[PDB]
Structure formats: C-alpha cells, structure tokens
Image (cartoon, rainbow, N blue to C red; front, side, top):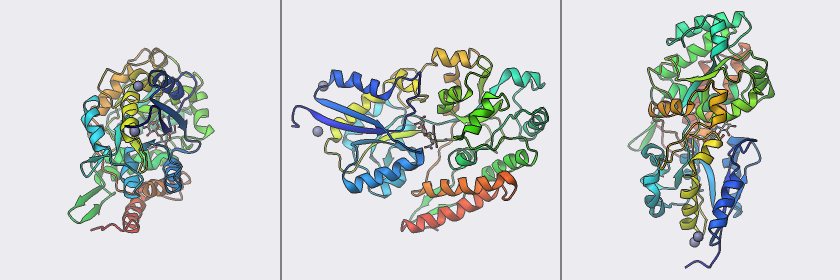
Length: 401
Ligand SMILES: CC(=O)N[C@@H]1[C@@H](O[C@@H]2O[C@H](CO)[C@H](O)[C@H](O)[C@H]2O)[C@@H](O)[C@@H](CO)O[C@H]1O
Ligand SMILES: [Zn+2]
Ligand SMILES: [Zn+2]
C-alpha cells in the first residue's frame, strides 16, 4: 500500500476568470476531505496549443504533473509521442459516470489514458434585438439566405459572422468535419482527405462573406475581437459552446439581455449536424507513480458538475444534469442556453484526429490569415491541410495510403 499521504499534481488550462468557481477552490474541497490524497492544481501559463509542448518537455525532464488537460484532438498525438499512462483498469471503474462518446475519446486501441471532461459542440451566438432592428426575423437556414442577411447587416456597419483566422484549425475543421471525417485508418495505412464536400461548402461560405466584407476578420483572442462585441458591431458569430462565459466577459456587458444561442444553420454543408471545436480529457502521464489515486481524484473532479459549468464547460459527466447559471440566462435574454448546448452535443458528428493534428491546425491558421486581405483563398486552408496532414503522418513514421 502507498504511505499515508499521496501527493498528486494536476495541470489544467481552464479559464479561472472572475465569477467562476476557481479550480483551486474546487481542489481545496477535495483536499479537506482527503488528507490521504493531496492535490496541487496549476493553470498552464501560455497559449492553449502550447500546453502539450510543455507536457512533452516536462515528461522528458521528469518534472511532469500526474494529470494534465489534453484535448480529444491532442490525445492521439501525445499518445504517439509516449507521454501517457495506460490507466484502463482504473478508468473502467468510473466509466458509468460519463457519456459513452466522450469516454471512447480517452481510448486508443481499447486502452484508456484518463477521463473525459467536457465537449465542444459548435453553436451560433447572436444579438436578437439587433437582428430585429435589421429586419432579420429568423435565423436564415441556408448559406445563400445567410449571406444575403450578412450583406444587409454589413451595409449598416454590423456583422452577423466573424472569420477567426487564429482559430481556423479548431473551429473551421469542426465546421467542415460536421459532415464527415478527414482521417481514417484503412488496415496498414492512414487515408487523408481534408477536401470533402463539407470543406468545400465551408470555404465557399466564408469566401463569399470575406469578399462581401460581411464578416469581421479580427483574430478571436486579440483585443480587437472583444472591441467588436463591446462596440456593438459584432452581433452574430459561430462559437464553441465553452465560449459562453468568455464571450460574456469579452462583451463588457454590451447586449446583456439580448444575446441568444441558436443551433448552426445549414451553412457549411453540415445538413443538420454540428461539429467539435475543442473538448478535452484529463490524462494520466507516462511516469505518474499514483495512477489509481490520480484517477480517484479525477473522477470526483470531473463530476463536480456545477463548478465545471461555471468554467463554461459542457460536462461529459452524466451523474447530474448541467444547469444554466443564473448569470448566463440573464445575459442571454433569459434563455436556458445549456439546453441548446445539449441539443448541439447530441447532433455533433464524430471526428477522428490523426496524430500530429497540431501541425495541421497550425498550418490552417497560417493559411486562414492569408485570406483576410485577399492574398489567399479560404479554400487554400483545406488544400494546405491535406499536404500538411500527409507530411506530418510521414514525419511521425506512419504509413499514408
Ligand atoms: C482546441 C483548443 O484547445 N481550443 C482552445 C480552447 O480550449 C478549450 O478551453 C475550454 C476552457 O475554456 C475547455 O477546456 C475546452 O475543452 C477546450 O478545448 C481555449 O483555451 C481558448 C482560449 O480561451 O483557446 C482555444 O484555442
Ligand atoms: Zn480520503
Ligand atoms: Zn498510489
């Protein structure tokens, strides 16, 4: 048996903003109850996509935490780099606490490497009051009807869409992937096709918007993006569901009481489906000496539903219903937005991510930014991703058809 006190470290990249139940305050509850398993949680200092590079540095060092946040999209990559610990015999005990889809996303080859934490269905945020002022009385459901509406808004200095070049890897992959995967294993080899009907539909949608000057082009994480919500010019956009409290903070309050969440329209060849953008597991890393207790704490952590929801998460836990915080429904015109997130989740297409997808995402972002001044086409996002996907798999020493 272990000694009396086991010490566990947990690195996460949860927002921890004002108004939220801070992770350390969540962990303090556990620590008080469990002197036998003491937990130290720390928030990664840096840009989200850099976290797994730090984990890689730290695994090789032997200064890694026991537990770290790992995106579903990042799991096959960090797995392939040998950063994870097979914890199947422990995962199996907690399996029933979690929805079956997210639980399958912590597995590689029928072994489990942690526990799912949340999901990232793409939805549409919009200011309903501002739509009304523009005579937009319905969320337009076809790409053509949306583009027509967006030109009308644009001529009044308003935008019902944003193009986010720094998020093309995560958001635009999800939107295209809503209608079919880009990657599959066929026997001995990966088969890559990132130029699906969905990719073509998605490209055409954003291309028409950009050519009409009818979408903002501020990078999502730049102060210019918050400025667009604050100044009232950005009145509609695709968003991952976990964006809700972020968006609310970014706004400064502008539109409070008027914002609403809708399902994505059929704008991306998505035909009634949505796609994933983010959503993460927490993984047990290669050389953790305490997998059992790490997983014991993690099952507790990932079932603190109201506290996770405070961080904007759509929890993977099925142990209790997630509920819209009062603050959020207020901001969103009294709407129970969590019901929208759950609907979106249930309509979210599966998407296998190749190992090395970080490189595909990084390239997508780079090529996405070329489109904002007309130097590049939106479509080039998908043709470049195809080449980077194939090259990255080959760099990993993996076979590609
Ligand atoms: C795919 C990805 O990593 N996207 C980044 C965001 O990550 C999401 O974060 C929320 C927490 O707010 C949640 O953990 C979700 O599972 C994640 O996918 C996020 O860090 C964002 C900055 O707020 O940047 C995105 O790039
Ligand atoms: Zn205890
Ligand atoms: Zn132990």
